[PDB]
Image (cartoon, grey):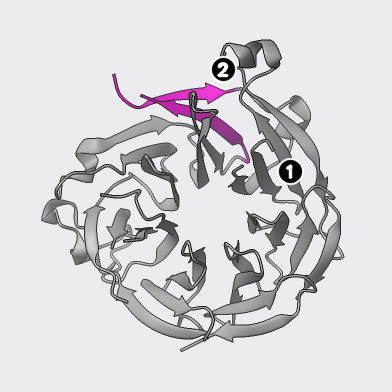
Amino acid sequence: KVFIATANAGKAHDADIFSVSACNSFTVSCSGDGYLKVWDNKLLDNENPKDKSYSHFVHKSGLHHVDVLQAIERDAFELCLVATTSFSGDLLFYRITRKKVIFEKLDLLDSDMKKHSFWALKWGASLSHRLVATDVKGTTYIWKFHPFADESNSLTLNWSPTLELQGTVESPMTPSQFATSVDISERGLIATGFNNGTVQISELSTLRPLYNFENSIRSVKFSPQGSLLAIAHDSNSFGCITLYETEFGERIGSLSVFAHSSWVMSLSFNDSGETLCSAGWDGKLRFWDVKTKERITTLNMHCDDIEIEEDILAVDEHGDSLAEPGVFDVKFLKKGWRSNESLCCVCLDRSIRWFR
């Protein structure tokens, strides 16, 4: 397979772009500058992404994670939610709607929850939608989202959302350590990565530990099937991918040629679960055939890739070259989301890039 550049935005944020997510309607990025940025997916015949972009300030501590949920509520109510976590440990919620794109901050968490310092997060789309998050102390949280507070509000489509804590699962290790990453599968499995190289899988709806196994985990992603778990982890300055069968937790394989000459920062399975994209701090997006565990293609990121020459960022804050900017995050987009499976990544040169 061959992936090609379709659109990009240089100097997209005023600070580092740590995380990116997408739904049918739009890609959303978040940055250490404190802003969310929404990017229309229905972009035109090579039109400037920035002209179809909408920013919203969230928290001056900066944002390090963002995920978007988009569904229709019984052919009636368009539901589009963004969750993002800040460096202060806050976990903020915004409803998104369309003169054009509007952000509405939601008050969902109680006082008890707000004492935690949230890190990683992930929506579990459709009986109600779920959300999962970690905090820095190593605990994972599981909520159920409701667009309507009671049935009277539901019967009138009266927006009044709540978040109901289903419970938590705790960190296996001696003293508890930083939980860097999370995911939730379609089959109902939760996986949590930690900064000591450990990973604990728990059962959703039980919320009880099933098992675990043992340098820091950076990303954790269930394949769409749910039968395989890909894990990015540091290992003596290099970045490694280890695959695990998901039932007993046996390691079944790995991806190499180590996976990246520097850290593997993020993972993203395509829709079929056949391809796996690795985002690397070496500034590479490598794609892996999952079944044969074999590298298929590589995209090398360069600061001079930016279509508008004016917002090429060739040098960082200290004078060091951004010739090959590391990739903070990557996400596969479904077939018909962009204007044929798409992809999006965000890199150290403060750029966001769409492909294929």
Q: Is residue 64 left or right of residue 17?
A: right
Vertical placement of residue 306 versus 206, above or below: below
Q: Is residue 90 found inside the magenta-colored segment of the image? A: yes
Q: Where is residue 259 shown, x and y percent of the image?
A: 50, 82
Considering only order in the chain, which callout, 2 or 1, is on the residue closer to the N terminus?
Answer: 1
Q: Which is nearer the eye, 26 or 58? A: 26
Instruction: Please name the residue shown 57% across and 11% down the image.
Output: 156
Vertical placement of residue 95 versus 333, above or below: above
Using the rendered image of the protein, determine whether residue 314 is visible from the camera's viewpoint.
Answer: no
Instruction: Please name the residue shown 43% across and 60% down the image.
Output: 330
Q: Where is residue 34 shown, x and y percent of the image?
A: 44, 38
Residue at numbered disc 2? 159
The amino acid type found where label 1 is placed reads Ile
Q: Spatial distance from mark 1 to mark 2, Cα to Cα?
A: 22 Å
Q: Which residues are magenta?
A: 89-106
- Tell me the element at label 2: loop
* Residue 14, label in figure: none
Vertical placement of residue 217 versus 336, above or below: below
Categorize mark 1 by other alpha carbons within 10 Å: few (<14), some (14-19), many (20+): many
Q: Is residue 201 found inside the magenta-colored segment of the image? A: no
Instruction: Please name the residue shown 72% across and 38% down the image.
Output: 143
Whether label 1 touches label 2, CB < 8 Å: no
Q: Is residue 280 left or right of residue 88?
A: left
- Tell me the element at label 1: strand
* Residue 142, label in figure: 1
Number of labels in the image equals: 2
